[PDB]
Length: 363
Image (cartoon, rainbow, N blue to C red; front, side, top):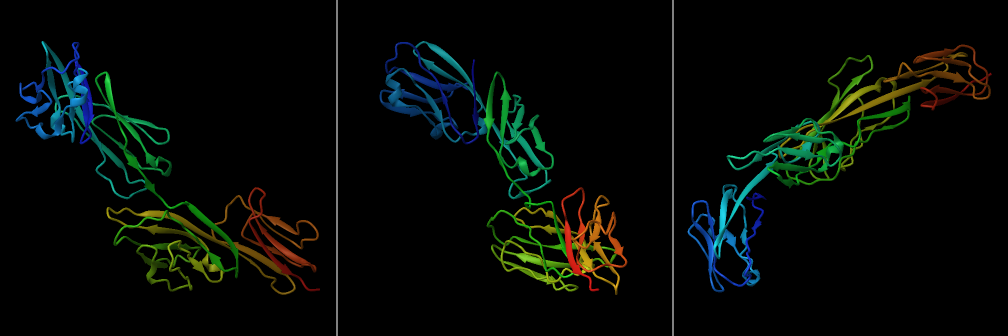
């Protein structure tokens, strides 16, 4: 018969009319033969039933034949077969509620799985097709969870609770925090004052965050090298640590890991791990630094690129004027016997110039 679905705490309207269309007696009773609400002229009445003060009928629409049933704050346990006994007939209506929910809630960063468990009347079965804000028609049973959330799955999903030839949609919101960059990379040269930058997406919240950056200097296995920072609103501050180089950090939220002079030993990888809370997790975002050193020995020269270079790149040294004085695929090339010209050291890959460091020759 009438099988209408509903959402927890939402509301729903049970129809009930008949011919004759005039203000006549009617009475809604559940399968337990208990009277939800009834009438006696304009005076609308209800019953002892648990549903009581959450049920209602539209007296205006009464005149036109409807003797509608409006259930407010939908209690899961409202799932029943109600009957609208109107003027000489019975209307059987089963209202099956549902309730899609994620328990892992508040402040979801990347990966950290999302879970969707469902509420339903003891005896009926649902099926959930969670359409994502972008693609993936992820579906499951009384439960379906999204694996490790990747940025693009941020937004508003639209899971559908299928049950019967009826179905009830659900709008759950899922936003994936996750730095706005994967592997940042900076190409500089022995001297150039290095800067780094990893942004977020504003937010407030109480006592919420701190982590640190870890670095794997090239060759210098001398790890445990780092800088630690605590954050609170648009306020950041180094917990302590730094040492080693003079890395300076900002007072302001848009973090700027500053490297005074790009000295050669400061080349390598790094992970900047952020971890805040309410219901924690820890963000990560990669960092890397390369250095180039163009320096003539005596009457003869050389230049070298340290750090995370690709086995696909090339280095070259020419005096600018004429073409390739030396072209090669490595990080420490040499050009013995140079001629006067403001020489350019070149690091690239494929074609587009990566690192460029100028220097002159004398005689």
